[PDB]
Image (cartoon, rainbow over all chains, first blue to last red; front, top):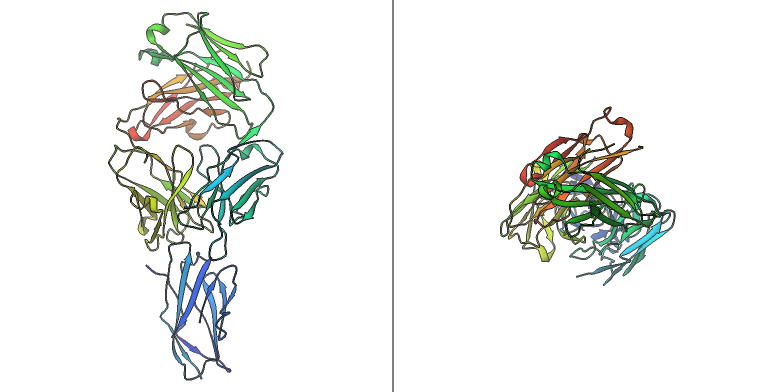
Length: 108
Length: 218
Length: 213
């Protein structure tokens, strides 16, 4: 009784320290209000707002349906480890929430 | 609670003109996410509702291009351009922004056509029913306009009264007309008692009242 | 494509309870939310609530929170609404309708709940038959039944043009009554054949009848 949030297992942070991975979910026809949060930056994707993490400059996100292509930039080595993606579908009521097993982001 | 008040309640419109309905909400319909959730439903007669426009101005798949929405805040408008017989029914606005979700009262869109005189037919009580002890003499006015008709029964050249009902078809979604029924409720004794049964039709399309009648036995 | 099939009509004595169904087909019952909409005879519509079949969560119209209990069953692709303390004003048409970018984008054909103290009673059908001209007339009178509703057809579905099934009129006997007619071309008198099919669910009175001069 929750949505099937799918992260990738281990993620290899990039040259300048920018990790990118897709966070997919399964009952994904509730697309109007869709807040996505990152736990070890968060934004709410609607129609008025289409590229998120405006208030979280270290993060980049592009929504389409059952996949969210994600980007955390500026990651140090002192940050490596467990990264989690939470998919809230605030509309229609009633909410329909989910969380993923996490991502080991190893910041070489 | 958010009240949706429509206008007009009835709205006659000739094929080819431009119908237009108004929905007014007690408080704004814009939701927090920025979207605005007005919906236009059309209930053709004896059918379940059907969806026409969502999120104010968007046509659900299948809805013809004559249909269109517009508005913002507390004031909205559905507008059929170039109406068609297929469009007759009741049109509801519905908001799905604030809980609880409410509907408008509706707007019966009537078609307006040229006068049409009714065909008249009359039906004597069925034999099986005559063996039941009751009897029903049924008179039919078929495909006329306007809805208004005078139906008068005459048994043996004197009119009865108090013992007949009327029923009226809803507007035809193909040819825009109405059809009427007159049922006369008599006991087997009173039916098997008189001779000449007559149904007189007076209608704004017939110059002279037209009558159809049967004599008990043919 | 999508089809929503609701249970038939139910006559329930007051103070009882009733639970109706909606049988989803042509789509993935858990994927999209589901609403129940009430339409009294007073024409205007009402929203009862919405239930997430994948989950069972609900959001209710506070004025129905006690009168209705909506529930789903994933193995049957079927949703359930249940009504406690059935009164006289609880009699309506009840609709299921499934979300799709919009609240009520697919509609169920409807469950007519009649809440009476009376006994169901069966229609009697009698051939409204034609006489001795271009185009002619035939029908089936459906006297004295209760409660509503009644379905009427001509040749199990074949005949459609020129039909006219009048609304039932309450009679002095406390009972509904109704006709159904259709105009056919004079020629086909003995060529084609005409039988109406009359169905009254709350008293299982399914009955075809032939109609002839």
